[PDB]
Image: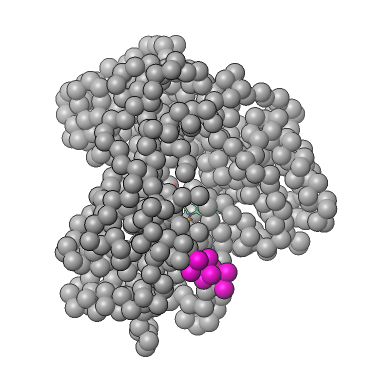
Amino acid sequence: SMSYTWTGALITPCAAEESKLPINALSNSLLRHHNMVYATTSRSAGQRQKKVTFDRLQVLDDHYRDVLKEMKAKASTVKAKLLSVEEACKLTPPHSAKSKYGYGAKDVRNLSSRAVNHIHSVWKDLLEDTVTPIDTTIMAKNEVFCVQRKPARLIVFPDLGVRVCEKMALYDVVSTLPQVVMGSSYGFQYSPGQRVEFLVNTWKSKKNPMGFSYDTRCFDSTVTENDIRVEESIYQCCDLAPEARQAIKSLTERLYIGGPLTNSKGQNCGYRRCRASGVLTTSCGNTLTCYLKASAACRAAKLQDCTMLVYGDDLVVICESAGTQEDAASLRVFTEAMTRYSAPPGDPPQPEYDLELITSCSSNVSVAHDASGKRVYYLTRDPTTPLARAAWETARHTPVNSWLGNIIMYAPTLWARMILMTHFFSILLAQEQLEKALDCQIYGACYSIEPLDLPQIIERLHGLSAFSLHSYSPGEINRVASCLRKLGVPPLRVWRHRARSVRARLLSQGGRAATCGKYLFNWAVKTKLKLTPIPYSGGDIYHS
Ligand SMILES: CNC(=O)c1c(-c2ccc(F)cc2)oc2cc(N(Cc3cc(F)c4c(c3)COB4O)S(C)(=O)=O)c(C3CC3)cc12
């Protein structure tokens, strides 16, 4: 079965699209090499269409069925509830795409009679009809990168009314089932500090640890009808209301397995027979499907004492080494098994014998030291894309503020602290916008967050140590320094000078502002203060 069929109609935009980095009076203070930063547009959609369109073959063996039976046995212990229309509505983001039938996201959130009436009719239709394919819109995503250019990724999503109905049927399922089925292997359950702790203790639990990342090429396209039906059979193991069972069956048959693709102008672009990236079950589905295939592939490879970590289509296995040559042999068998299950790799997997050399979800573990001199592990990444996006966001207001998301999730890193915090707090000070809530996206969920609350948020996610880390590793410092030279960002010495000023300015304002000065910028001062404590990817999900 081909992942997609195409009619020839183009994937069209719904608004003007910029590819070139916008420049304002603040741009050069962050980044000088402007031509290295670009945004993707619908003009490259055709190139992506070629990449994501291919034939899938699946061969399923006993290892696959054995693991599935185990997953279903765990799923059988889960009890999930239907959300009411009101509850589902409150989970709808304020800036979620409006319905084709005369209401928007704010009408949903307000429980307006028109929006509520349509939702009730869509739900009734799901209960009454389990066959008619549901329409979807296909769009090119506009995302920002540094050169070496990527073609635009594609998003596929149904109408707002359907999206609310997905929440009613499945929000409690996708929120509760994966952790029960996959246990400690389900990566979404951890804060950044908990995840790094899990990874470290997992590495030390093995006598001779070996680990590897495995990244599938265009995972969404490798997901077959079988895969999506097997996912449904897992959901249906739950203790559910009969009305929920029918809605889940209907959504699977009419939406999740496949459907027609329509562009922004209303033309049929073709047909999908693989994972839709903009449905509620995308994250949960990919995570279950990746975990199933990978667990079965570990058994085929005879890998000893495996601990897996899975987040969507991102996979890491840490296991007991059988020797360097034996380990390398077993990874080939793994890849062969994964390939028979439809999930061949982008690059072949590599065994690693140092935890810090495994990269996954674009991240790796590194080490720094706290105020006492004790080693502290933390998750970091190559800062090139965060910084390119920060540059765009310096001159353009965007729907999601990646800089804010990055400060929160990478708070302990030397690049988030020295550059992102310093740059954006300076901007916020100048416009007196410290108290203004901003949208950012964490694990695919949209959150509205006031910058003034960052200290409390960072402590809870990473611990108090995130405000006093020092003596970073030579490898991490060198990667950061090299990235700055590459993009024409000023060197770290300049950012320390700027941070002193930004800190002084925050202290001057007092209150929560001064708390941001004290905690976020203690690294900048020569004589430190002793810091005490402070008193659904594509799923269309929102939280306060
Ligand atoms: C690969 N599997 C894992 O679970 C992860 C490893 C990893 C595992 C094993 C290794 F050996 C090395 C790294 O490192 C990780 C780092 C993160 N973070 C970064 C991050 C990545 C993202 F894609 C997103 C977000 C954050 C927010 O919203 B996004 O969807 S972090 C520092 O916030 O914790 C995550 C996040 C998304 C859950 C997972 C892993």
Point 41% across, 11% down: residue: 132
Residue 395 at least partly seen? yes
**Left or right of 89 on screen, residue 33:** right
* Image x and y of residue 463, in percent: 44, 68
Q: Does the magenta stretch include residue 477?
A: yes
* Image x and y of residue 53, in percent: 54, 25
Compared to residue 257, the image places residue 533 above or below, namely: below
Point 26% across, 36% down: residue: 16
* Image x and y of residue 12, in percent: 34, 27
Residue 172 at least partly seen? no
Q: Does the magenta stretch include residue 234?
A: no
Q: Quadrant of residue 531?
A: bottom left
Q: In which quarter of the image is residue 104?
A: top left
Q: How many labels does the image show?
A: 0
Compared to residue 267, the image places residue 45 above or below, namely: below
Range covered by the magenta-colored residues: 474-482
Nearest the camera: 470 or 373? Answer: 470
Q: Is the magenta stretch mostly helix, strand or loop?
A: helix
**Left or right of 227 on screen, residue 36:** left
**Left or right of 104 on screen, residue 446:** right
Compared to residue 410, the image places residue 314 above or below, namely: above
Q: Residue furthest bottom?
A: 527
**Left or right of 169 on screen, residue 365:** right
